[PDB]
Image (cartoon, rainbow, N blue to C red; front, side):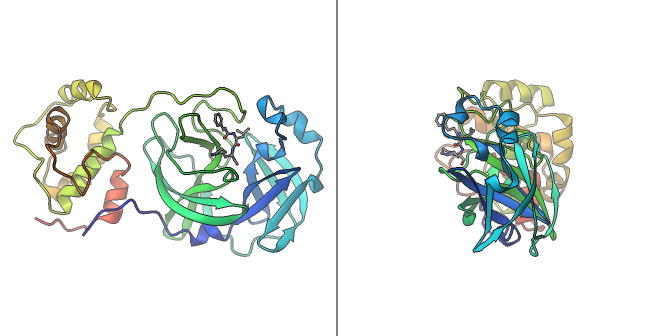
Amino acid sequence: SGFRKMAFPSGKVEGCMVQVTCGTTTLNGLWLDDTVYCPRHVICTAEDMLNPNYEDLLIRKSNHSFLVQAGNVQLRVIGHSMQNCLLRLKVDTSNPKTPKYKFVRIQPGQTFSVLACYNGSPSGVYQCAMRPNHTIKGSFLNGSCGSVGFNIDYDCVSFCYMHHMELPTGVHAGTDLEGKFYGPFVDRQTAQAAGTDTTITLNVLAWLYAAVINGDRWFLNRFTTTLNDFNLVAMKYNYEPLTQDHVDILGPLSAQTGIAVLDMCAALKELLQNGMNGRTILGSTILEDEFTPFDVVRQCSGVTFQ
Ligand SMILES: CC(C)C[C@H](NC(=O)/C=C/c1ccccc1)C(=O)N[C@H](C=O)C[C@@H]1CCCNC1=O
């Protein structure tokens, strides 16, 4: 029993982290096979960062403008290209610790683990949700760029995030591993603000199902709701609308608990209108939205505490 924000084991990812220096800027890179990936703003100076032209800044560099270090061992750069907001550095050694892996662009509301790294050295692991407004509420200091987010399925690492910047509100923005940003953000020190965010309705429901699987039913009720009547309540409390696709996705959790999705929505509707009355759900005094339905099935017992 119990329920925690759980990251994936980070070992397979730790063996891919390196340090990338160019000029005076240093950040982390990701070494798969004979390529190292890292944010392209590694080629900026302090004055470049306000309005960089990366194409112009890059052509002024050679292969040996870039210093790549894997632990102790220096790695020789023998090629370089810019892919969207990333640089791809070809090196002369293929990483013997390369795991099976894919590059994936995750969807809003999905979760992943972040390995926070400094100077190519892993420092910490934690779980994140891609917010609706395409930021993540991470914990990143200077030098954390090039840290990656990932999921692990069996033995395959699905890389989905690389860290580039922090917004004025203290949340974080970055790209997939093809260099396309999540959200309308650009890699410049310009005025950039997070769009307004929304609570991830699908995840709140998934976590209510977690609470039932772990043996708690106090928040349920005898009512039910139409999709549309729920969405009128979702609107008032700044929750995402529930769609029929979201109802379908909650199918298995509804089966394992015997609670119909729209029954659970009535429960949530009532929770949004009346509060929690000083009680907790799975240890929390607030409604949690950073667990997907997949998160719940992964972590919870497949047998309900009836
Ligand atoms: C987009 C790029 C041109 C540079 C990038 N810029 C930024 O992250 C923006 C920082 C900022 C702070 C306050 C107000 C407005 C902007 C950067 O330094 N990125 C760091 C990468 O190493 C990581 C930043 C550092 C700050 C502290 N936390 C973080 O995530």
